[PDB]
Image (tube, coloured by chain):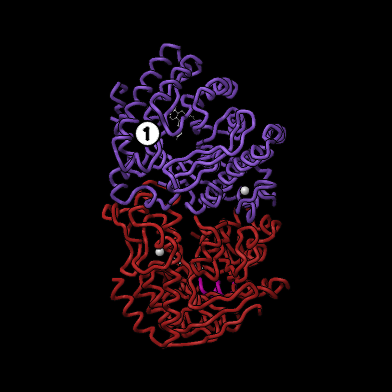
Chain colours: A purple, B red
């Protein structure tokens, strides 16, 4: 397999469906990447069984303990965790800034160290070290922030390219900033493209602006990215967010909602989310969802999961989390197929009429 | 299959190996029964994969929530949890008493209600409602306690036998009390046998007396039970306890140690237990145990599990617990085979020289 190849097999409007080929495996796009030294409460085989092709490696926690160098000593994150498929590592910056300088962030994490850490973990897809601009932001602060990020983008690329083994086997994504301002988004897209990356993320959204605002910015911002490269909307999100995003040209997603929300009693369904802790589910013998193909909906009822979650049982987290990650993957498959058959617009309208 | 059949296929000294056949499945004896509306942090298929033939149903918690009647409404514990094999339910008394009267315990749980609850849960093996005598106990208090238990034993049998469906499909075990006193143990064994039960438990041990004392009492007490019926040592215990107990004629065991201890960082190994949280394991690429056949020892290292447990990760509990339950079952298989080939005494000496 090549180091990195993105091919689009079908389109409808702005939406695309296809594949990213990498040495460790093929990624079906639009893709949802579950967030992780584990994906909470799940074995990798379980994650794989749900249909995940790739997972997102939580660099900030790992960097802490057991540490990037230790994991490298132990053989890399893949071996450590037992996942042999692609891993996208974030740069550690979002969570750090959640003392700032041109060098990087003291809390010292810089683009160079960020790249080195992701290399030590053995990431397949490395993110450039950026700064997610707070919302709201004034045009000046938005610009100043973006401009620094573009500088950090160049250092990341140079850093990445300076390590032979990393450049030959991994891929590097660049991240667009510019808050909600078109001119700034364009300047950012221009800079990233001149540097050159394997993929392009849309940064700085899912920061408190709301869906209407997020979609308006995606409307002008995603066409600014190279068409022939994957488009990654960072930290999004709810089902309805992913559908609308795909409608605007996004190929990739990461979010903690399925996992976090799962342990909290929220289950995703085609008729919308439910909180299984509700008394209404105490004797409901139906599965979490009507149509879900997951193992959980195959073998346990609402009633059981309700009790487990009410009880604080670990098994509760496990089952809720497995269903939710399966549901997200099923969502992506439906997105992929509907695009493939040129029926995505209707799927997106049918999805929303039922989900809401 | 019959409602209940115990057959001994081999012996060595006091030790026996064989099978209990029941409608829901065969139990290989000596048996270890993992303790549970779940077996913490494990799916039933995982429990089964470790080699468990039967699990112990925690009546006291279930009785609380979601309640015995609700579970019956939902189809019984087997369906609820997703375990289709035999289930032994305790009577709820140990944990309750951990206001006393001849009727039962107010906290009101009586032999009659205890039996009814176990019936509502759909237990395959029902325990009589007893009172585990505190240790130490004077001969008078030991006697008074035992005598009440024998009375409660008779009510349990009558209760059980009064429900056609329960008597036709389940089995009933009686429990020996008498603290550490031989004469009292004999009187208890006599009473239980005159009433008649499908199996006989040795109650009132594993209460703070220590192994030397527990073994001395087992030495005279287990031969007091009917030879042709299974012998269940309640709430035991560590590996070394189970070996010595089997040496004295015990066929069945339950204990929380594998599960509890697992979530706490204690892993069982053939060279003795280890606490995986120890810094020494931070870069140890070996599996928890040298020879264990479990899936965990197949795929993850000490280092990884150490980090997970240090991190408070659910996956940590899951893996530690699966290994520990697998280790206990592997212990039982080795016990069963060694007995089968008449080499148990040497296995017990080889086990202890290595384990200690
Ligand atoms: O610009 C960004 N740069 C880098 N990371 C971002 C993240 C973290 C994505 N989730 C990873 C773990 C974001 N998460 C959200 N919302 C949730 N917005 C985000 C924006 C950025
Ligand atoms: O006599 C007894 N009668 C009934 N239950 C007993 C228990 C609970 C066994 N574990 C089930 C859950 C015991 N656990 C221990 N030690 C631990 N001693 C026990 C003695 C008795
Ligand atoms: Zn499901
Ligand atoms: Zn093991």
**Vertical comparison of A65 with B18: above or below:** above
Q: Position of residue A198 (x, y in %)?
A: 43, 34
Relative depth, front residue between B308 and A87 = A87
Q: Which residue of the protein is positioned furthest toward the left in this rendering? A: B280
Q: Residue at x 57, y 82 (%)?
A: B6
SS majority, magenta: helix
Q: Residue at x 44, y 74 (%)?
A: B332
Q: Is A138 left or right of A72, judged from the image as shown?
A: right
**Vertical comparison of B288 with A330: above or below:** below
Counting the numbered discs, the total is 1
Q: Position of residue B49 (x, y in %)?
A: 51, 66
Q: Position of residue A299 (x, y in %)?
A: 63, 56
Give the quarter of the image for residue B220: bottom left
Report if residue B135 is visible in the image.
no
Instruction: Name the residue beneath numbered marker 1.
Output: A92
Relative depth, front residue between B209 and B199 = B199
**Vertical comparison of B294 with A97: above or below:** below
Q: Is B40 left or right of A121, judged from the image as shown?
A: right
Beta carbon of the mark 1 residue lies under 8 A of ligand 1: no
Relative depth, front residue between A341 and B238 = A341
Tell me the subunit letter for badge 1: A
| Quadrant into which the C terminus of chain B falls | bottom left
Q: Which residues, given as a range, are shown in magenta?
A: B145-152
Q: Count residues near mark 1 (Cα–Cα under 10 Å), then give few for <14, some for 14-19, many for 20+.
A: many
Q: Is A244 left or right of B30, judged from the image as shown?
A: right
Report if residue B334 is visible in the image.
yes
| Quadrant into which the N terminus of chain B falls | bottom right
Q: Is B83 left or right of A353, judged from the image as shown?
A: left
Q: Position of residue A224 (x, y in %)?
A: 51, 22
Q: Residue at x 42, y 53 (%)?
A: A82
């Amino acid at each position: 397999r090549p180091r990195f190849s993105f091919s689009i097999a079908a389109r409808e409007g702005k939406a695309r469906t296809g594949t990213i080929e990498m040495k460790r495996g093929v990624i079906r796009t639009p893709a949802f990447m579950p967030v992780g030294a584990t994906v909470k409460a799940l074995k990798p085989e379980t994650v794989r069984a749900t249909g995940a092709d790739i997972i997102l490696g939580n660099t900030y926690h790992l960097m802490l303990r057991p540490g990037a160098e230790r994991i490298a000593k132990l053989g890399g994150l893949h071996s450590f965790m037992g996942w042999d498929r692609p891993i996208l590592t974030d740069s550690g910056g979002y969570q750090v800034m959640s003392k700032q300088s041109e060098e990087g962030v003291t809390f010292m994490l810089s683009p160079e160290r960020s790249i080195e850490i992701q290399h030590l973990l053995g990431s397949d897809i490395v993110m450039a070290f950026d700064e997610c601009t707070p919302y709201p932001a004034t045009p000046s602060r938005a610009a100043s922030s973006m401009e620094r990020s573009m500088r950090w983008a160049k250092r990341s690329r140079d850093a990445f390219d300076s390590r032979k083994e990393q450049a030959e086997n991994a891929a590097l994504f660049g991240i667009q900033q510019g808050s909600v301002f078109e001119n700034l988004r364009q300047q950012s897209a221009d800079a990233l493209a001149e540097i050159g990356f394997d993929g392009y993320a849309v940064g700085g959204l899912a920061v408190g602006e709301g869906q209407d605002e997020m979609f308006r910015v995606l409307d002008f911002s995603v066409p600014m990215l190279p068409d022939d490269k994957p488009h990654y909307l960072m930290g999004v999100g709810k089902p309805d967010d992913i559908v609308g995003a795909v409608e605007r040209g996004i190929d990739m997603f990461d979010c903690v909602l399925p996992t976090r929300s799962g342990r909290n009693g929220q289950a995703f369904t085609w008729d919308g989310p439910i909180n299984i802790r509700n008394a209404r589910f105490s004797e409901d013998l139906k599965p979490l969802d009507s149509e879900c193909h997951c193992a959980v909906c195959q073998k346990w009822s609402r009633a059981y999961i309700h009790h487990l979650i009410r009880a604080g049982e670990i098994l509760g987290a496990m089952l809720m989390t497995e269903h939710n990650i399966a549901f997200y993957q099923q969502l992506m498959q439906k997105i992929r197929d509907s695009i493939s058959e040129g029926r995505f617009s209707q799927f997106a309208q049918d999805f929303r009429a039922r989900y809401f």
